[PDB]
Image (cartoon, rainbow, N blue to C red):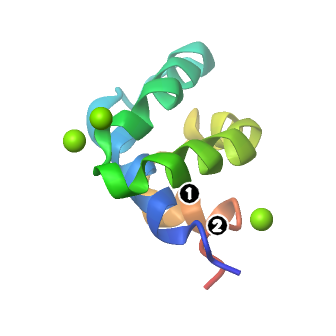
Amino acid sequence: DGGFCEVCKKLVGYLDRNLEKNSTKQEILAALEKGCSFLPDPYQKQCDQFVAEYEPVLIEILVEVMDPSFVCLKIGACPS
Ligand SMILES: [Mg+2]
Ligand SMILES: [Mg+2]
Ligand SMILES: [Mg+2]
């Protein structure tokens, strides 16, 4: 239903900017645990929920691609 689309693009964007493209799954899991704290406060709890719900698919995809619009489309967070 796209309810996490905007927060997905913001948190994957944080990672896209701040993680190397070469990153290990362990490196991405650690970044996912910290990423929501870097978003504006109104997104904080939504981002925590998003990351907990999508963590498995996020780790699988982010080792291959970190573009926010693509990642969020591919995992279903942004249905377009
Ligand atoms: Mg739901
Ligand atoms: Mg802040
Ligand atoms: Mg705070």
In percent of width and height, residue 73 lies at 60, 69
Residue at screen point 44% across, 48% down? 12
Question: Quick one: 55 or 73, which is closer to the camera?
Answer: 55
Question: Quick one: 48 or 75, which is closer to the camera?
Answer: 48
The vertical placement of 11 against 79, above or below, is: above
The vertical placement of 43 against 39, above or below, is: below
Q: Residues within 10 Å of mark 1 (few under 14, many from 20)?
A: many
In percent of width and height, residue 76 lies at 70, 67
Q: Quadrant of the C terminus?
A: bottom right
Question: Quick one: 17 or 43, which is closer to the camera?
Answer: 43
Residue at screen point 58% across, 32% down? 63
Tag 2 secondary structure: loop
> Nearer the viewer's eye, disc 2 or disc 1?
2
The residue beneath circle 1 is: 71
The vertical placement of 14 against 75, above or below, is: above
Residue at screen point 54% across, 54% down? 46
Residue at screen point 35% across, 28% down? 19
Which quadrant of the picture is home to ligand 1?
Answer: bottom right
First in residue order: circle 2 vs circle 1 = 1
In percent of width and height, residue 52 lies at 69, 39
Badge 2 amino acid: Ala
Q: Quadrant of the N terminus?
A: bottom right
Badge 1 amino acid: Val
Q: Residues within 10 Å of mark 2 (few under 14, many from 20)?
A: many
Q: How far separated are the C-alphas under marks 2 and 1?
A: 9 Å
In percent of width and height, residue 42 lies at 36, 57
Tag 1 secondary structure: helix
Question: Quick one: 7 or 20, which is closer to the camera?
Answer: 7
The residue beneath circle 2 is: 77
